[PDB]
Amino acid sequence: NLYFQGAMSIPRSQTTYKKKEGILTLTEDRKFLIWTPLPATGPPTVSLALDNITNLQQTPPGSAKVILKFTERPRPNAEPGAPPPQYMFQFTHPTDARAEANAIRDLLSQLLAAA
Ligand SMILES: [Cl-]
Ligand SMILES: [Cl-]
Ligand SMILES: [Cl-]
Ligand SMILES: [Cl-]
Ligand SMILES: [Cl-]
Ligand SMILES: [Cl-]
Ligand SMILES: [Cs+]
Ligand SMILES: [Cs+]
Ligand SMILES: [Cs+]
Ligand SMILES: [Cs+]
Ligand SMILES: [Cs+]
Ligand SMILES: [Cs+]
Ligand SMILES: [Cs+]
Ligand SMILES: [Cs+]
């Protein structure tokens, strides 16, 4: 009858969003995926509630870029043919890009299924 929560630390990963460099992480409550542009002392420019995330995709290993793509629920007044909102983050750590992507992906998938 035991219940366990995830206990891996929250990563802060070097990532590019809409061609600007920044940091992808989660809020301390693990409810929001947040991206903040460098220097990273301002507020996030992307804040995605894990409750609104509907898919998580990745470039396959050996691709030119390491990218995670998060899809969000359609916005309330979107037209029915419109694509859903999406957010692509390219991992730019020179050696650890794919490792960091995997770590975020794993943490996110665990949280998404836990909720
Ligand atoms: Cl959003
Ligand atoms: Cl949900
Ligand atoms: Cl790769
Ligand atoms: Cl609608
Ligand atoms: Cl996995
Ligand atoms: Cl769930
Ligand atoms: Cs890191
Ligand atoms: Cs969700
Ligand atoms: Cs889903
Ligand atoms: Cs790569
Ligand atoms: Cs809609
Ligand atoms: Cs976007
Ligand atoms: Cs970098
Ligand atoms: Cs659950």
Image: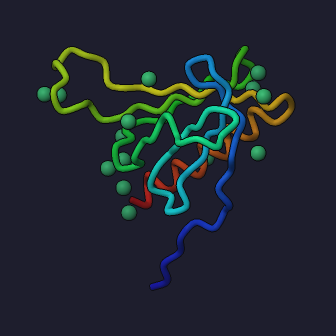
From the viewer's side, name the closer residue of 30 and 41.
Answer: 41
On screen, residue 71 versus residue 20, left or right, reads: left
Q: Is residue 64 above or below residue 67?
A: above
- Give how far across and how far down residue 60 sits, in percent: 65, 24
Please tell me which residue is depicted at 16% across the width and 19% down the height of the picture: 80
Quadrant where ligand 11 appears:
top left
From the viewer's side, name the closer residue of 92 and 18.
Answer: 18
Q: Is residue 49 above or below residue 5?
A: above
- Give how far across and how far down residue 37 sits, in percent: 62, 32
- Give how far across and how far down residue 66 sits, in percent: 69, 25
On screen, residue 43 versus residue 76, left or right, reads: right
- Give how far across and how far down residue 19 sits, in percent: 61, 17
- Position of the N terminus, as image quadrant, is bottom left
Please tell me which residue is depicted at 50% across the width and 34% down the height of the picture: 45
Please tell me which residue is depicted at 68% across the width and 60% down the height of the picture: 9
What kind of colouring is applied to the model shown? rainbow
From the viewer's side, name the closer residue of 53 and 48.
Answer: 48
Q: Quadrant of residue 74?
A: top left
From the viewer's side, name the closer residue of 98 and 87.
Answer: 87
- Position of the C terminus, as image quadrant, is bottom left
On screen, residue 82 versus residue 29, left or right, reads: left
Q: Quadrant of residue 75?
A: top left
